[PDB]
Image (cartoon, coloured by chain):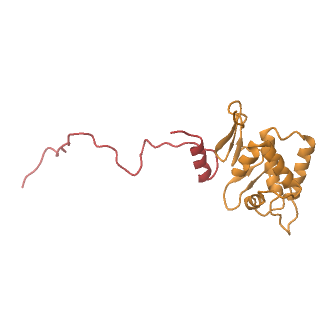
Amino acid sequence: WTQMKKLPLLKEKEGPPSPWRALLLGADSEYIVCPPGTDQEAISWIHSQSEI
Amino acid sequence: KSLLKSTILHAERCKEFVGNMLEEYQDPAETTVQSLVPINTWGKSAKRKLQEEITSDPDWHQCPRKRAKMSYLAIIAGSIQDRDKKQTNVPRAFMLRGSQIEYDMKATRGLVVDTTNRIIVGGETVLREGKGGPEGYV
C-alpha cells in the first residue's frame, strides 16, 4: 500500500488548436433587428433589403 | 403584396381600382380583395371615407401615401360584408385572412411601412424618394 503527496498533473496534448464544432455558433451568435410581424414578413424584409 | 405593388406604382391602376371598388363595378381583382379581408361590417363606412377623400382632394392620385390610403380603404370597402351584424366604423388596422399579417391605414407598421424617405411594401422598398423613380427610362 502506498500513499501520495503530489496531486496528479494532467498532461496537455500539443498540436493544432481544435476548431469550433457544434450545432450553432455560441458566443459569436448575433441577430438582425426586424420590424414587427410574422416570420414570413421578417424573412421577406431580410431577403428584399440585403445583398450578399 | 402584388396587388399593393400594382396600385402604388401606377396612378392609373390606382384610379381604376378605386373606381371599380367604390361603385361595385367589375374589378379584375375582386377575388383577391374578397380573399384578403375577413367577413366584417366596414363596407359602407369605408365607401363613405372614400367619398370624403375624393371630394376633398380630387387630385389625390399622385401622392403615393394618398394612393396607399385610398387602396386600403377600397380593399376594406369591397370585402365580404356580414349579413347580420350592423355596420361599424372602419378600424385603423385589420388582420388578413388565415394569417397574422396586419394591414394598417397610416402604414406605420405591418405589411406597408411608409417613412418620409421611402415606402416599403411586404418587406421590399417599392418606392425610394429622391432616387430611382417608379417609371423606367427611354
Residue A32 appears at what percent x and percent y? Answer: 55, 42
Taking the spot 54% from the left edge, 39% from the top edge, the residue there is: A51
Q: Colour of chain A?
A: red
Residue B47 appears at what percent x and percent y? Answer: 88, 54
Furthest residue in direction top, as rendered: B130
Q: Is residue A19 left or right of residue B107?
A: left
Residue B48 appears at what percent x and percent y? Answer: 90, 52
Reply above or below: B117 against B109. Answer: above
Q: What is the quadrant of residue B134 in the picture?
A: top right
Taking the spot 68% from the left edge, 54% from the top edge, the residue there is: B101
Furthest residue in direction left, as rendered: A1
The reply to whether residue B32 is in sight is: yes
Front in this rendered view, residue B12 or B125: B12
**Which chain is in orange here?**
B
The reply to whether residue B69 is in sight is: no
Q: Is residue A4 left or right of residue B105?
A: left
